[PDB]
Length: 603
Ligand SMILES: [Ca+2]
Ligand SMILES: [Zn+2]
Image (cartoon, rainbow, N blue to C red; front, side, top):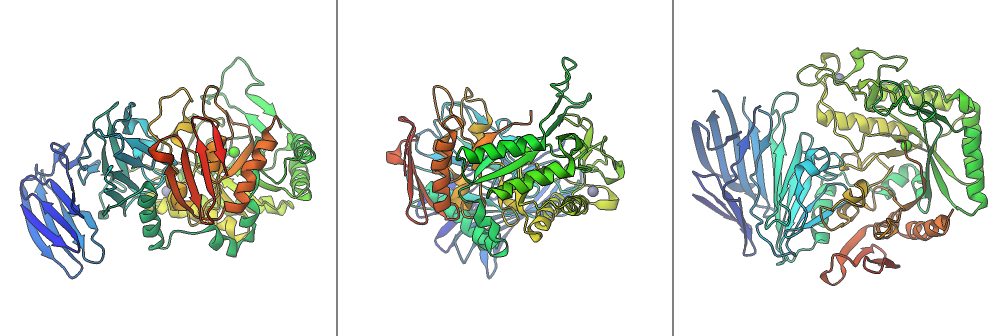
């Protein structure tokens, strides 16, 4: 049993049982009784080590315990758990030495009850999940198994807050092969939240580091402010302002209303979406001519300022032939009708973006070669046929920019000036690992190659879009398809995982523009309230791949956007401790209040 006191915090670490605990400002947190730090293969505790060494350490930078673990059959690794002098933070390092996952640090005890002490997780826009919450919240119920750099982990942190206002945030400083793990039992007494780490390309390769910061007199607002600061203290908090200094078009997205509609549909036979009764469900076409007149009419009706995202615009048809997604669909009016539509949009003060796809790599593609595809760490090629274009694998992001550069050249060759562009999935799904000797790529590398893809667009004054908003992309992404809450991605019938809190826009409102769902759910929540509280852009039309007081509703949300769209969301609060009735405050003092009993808002 070692003990360390440094810079206002105290660390405790048990020599023999491995359970560690920290304290600062008189609040103690502790590893749960009965959860071992583990390794996995086809589960061994750390204590399972044939040899275990512990060395007390004082460096000029902090103090703590280094531990070596050999054994298990031959394998070895190391942990370093220390207090940083400058700040008071505790840092946990797992250190390869030479295995499927690593679950370490072991989760902190946050049992139990007391409806007001909450877990904050980062699964899409925030989820504030109180310890007494009725519904079960597990990792199986979280997108992509709770994996950072995805929809299941918008930001590489989680946090636990007590009624006391005594919190800890946990920041993953090595996210690219990592995620968090959540166990909140239905109505549970406790919520346990823990970090997990996977090998990169078959091997734990690089050290993995978690940074804990204990907070006192703490808000959920404040917990997000800590991360924001961490991010900027590392130069990855890219504002719209910074983006705007390079491409002022960023400013033209404020106040805009979103129209998402498409041109061609063409479900293939091998596709999961194919049924033989009937075709015509499998084939549909709306022409450029029709979308022209659509956009015409929306202006005439007073829709206002608009951005048109255009699905299915190329010849093979929506979700077909990627990356050979050329030419612009003939049967809808070829390059010409497309050219004419784009012209028309600009001609009435409206913006336009293409829908494109560079991860999904179809066999039906004109240029398909298995030589350009992903190979997993076991050297296999992944295959599915979930989507419209049928059989596919994934294109190694190592080759992604080649294809972005080639395609958008062709597009521009035909007098088409894209305002924006949407490269699909990049910002929602995980980075691939690629083991192909001819283009080896780690998950870290994959996000950089995706960002290189975005940056080519930015270089051509073409704004940037993708599915969702995983923070890796923050420096190269202008806007998204949405940054919704988890509950908006489930049937409104589904029991929810917690209180919706805008944890993300708390961190990035002033960095990435998001359109929002405008739906009303019968017998419940109007999704306009969430757009408001999140100071976002409104959807007017949202035609899915698989007007009626709308304009009047949009123009409310749009107007607030123009005022606030680039500003920091400084505060979000729950009016009088009640989960419904929430307030969010922006940089310029604007307070959007939203009553969830009354379905009302106040601007
Ligand atoms: Ca789309
Ligand atoms: Zn590759």
